[PDB]
Length: 55
Length: 55
Length: 76
Image 1: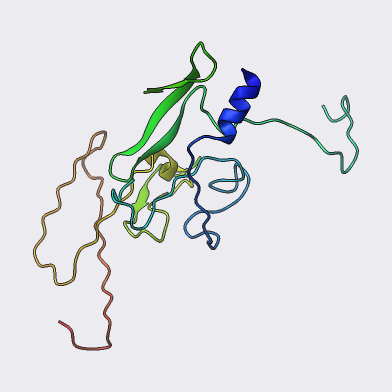
Image 2: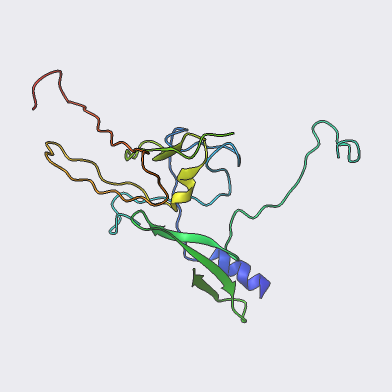
């Protein structure tokens, strides 16, 4: 079961968003207590021409 | 604490952190109109299907 | 002693939309709700309806409206 769910995770439905941005625009990138977010944190994004534009 | 557990300069301190929250409370999506949707994931008894409960 | 959570709300999408006098992270408590809507060009009379709970008489809010023109003159 563990080996199969490792293969399940390799074959999941997924999305990703690679973005290029300046710091403090508006968010500060830095460790917890100093930035709004850091590596590993959950962040939201919107997609420009996606059919439901508030998603 | 610094006298009881002395650590040298440059000592590499390993930790493991949960920056997901999938198994307790987090959000997988939402709307800019009404906010993020709070949710939990649980593995069902087969070990392969995850249920999602919305808070 | 810190200032109270007196706030500036800014509707502009380029900036932090809620900021407190205390430096408290009040914008993180919005659950990703955003202000989305501008006042359009050549907008005349508008009525803004606010509501408040937990306030006392003598406190004021303000509404603040910029004036940015494409040109040094004309366009009224």
